[PDB]
Each structure stands twice: as structure tokens, then as C-alpha cells.
Image (tube, rainbow, N blue to C red; front, top):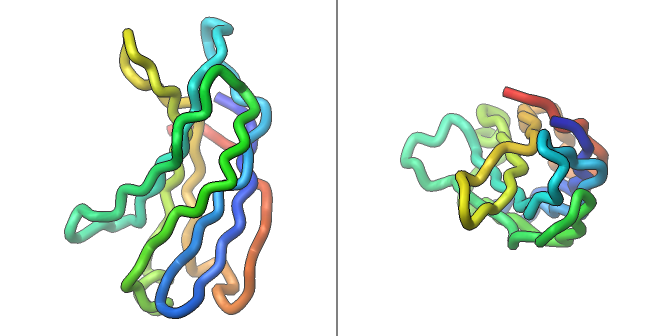
Length: 125
């Protein structure tokens, strides 16, 4: 577990925008290059509908995604009662997908009237 993810987070027209830009310095226990993708949830997830994820970036510890994850139909009031749970996992075809690191971000901490671009350190459980 290690590394850091750069995100751009904003809100416009009743929609939350999470831009996954890139990740640096992912590590694996056995030293082989992972196949990272990013998955996010908005928690708590009453209806169990909030999974979003990026494409897989293959064979790299420093993936660039520049992908936008979109959450529609939420008011800021509701969002301030949610946390964004971000996971980085390796896509594996011959073994279980495994956890490379994550970060949980209470959305109340953001100024959702502007765009916030920032680096976040990835951690364990």
C-alpha cells in the first residue's frame, strides 16, 4: 500500500464531477506491475447504486486516467451527508483483483462552489 492520486472535484447543475487524473507510486507485495483501475462509492448508499469506475490502465505503477466519474441527481445537502470512498485495485485475470490503496473523503469538507484539484495519499483498510 502506497502512492497518491490526483483528483479534480466539482459540482454543477445537480451533478458531482470526480476527475481521476493520475496516480503515482503504486506498490505491490510481489513486485509485479499491477493493472490499476479506480472505483468509487458514495457512502452510505441506500439504494446500492453508487459504484463508478475508470478503465483499467495496464502494467503500470503510475497510471494516467483523465477520466470523469459522474454522480447525478444529488443535492449538495445530500452530498454533505456522504463520503466518497475511493479504491485503487489491480485487475487480474488469473487471481483475485487486489487492493492497491484507497482514501475516504467526507464531501462536506469541499467547497462545491468551486473546482478543487488536489493530491491524496492512498492508505490501507
